[PDB]
Image 1 (tube, rainbow over the protein chains, first blue to last red):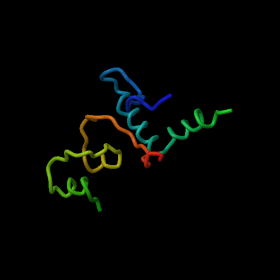
Image 2 (tube, rainbow over the protein chains, first blue to last red):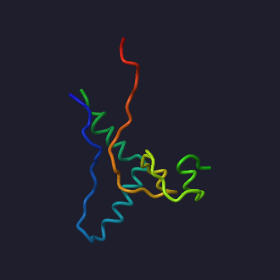
Image 3 (cartoon, chains in turn orange, brown):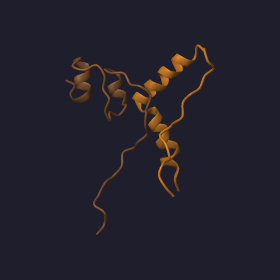
Image 4 (tube, chains in turn purple, green):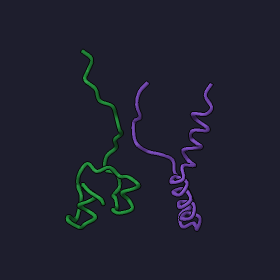
Length: 50
Length: 50
């Protein structure tokens, strides 16, 4: 019954100082470039309506 | 060839851009961005119905 209240999203979270933070962030950015994230969004949100 | 706000920034004609300049990934490759000071979104505008 209305528009969005703010502009915030979801981010992959890791423990502070973890070695996995930078590689996972790079993978997220590259997949955003590759469009796999939008493809999964289409598959699960738009491609599952009946 | 960049132009506009980013064009002035890249060629070093000015030091700081303080304007309604939206943070985008493509601009991040040539200029840096601060944290968002306000939230917004793209909307549609028409003349109100007579």
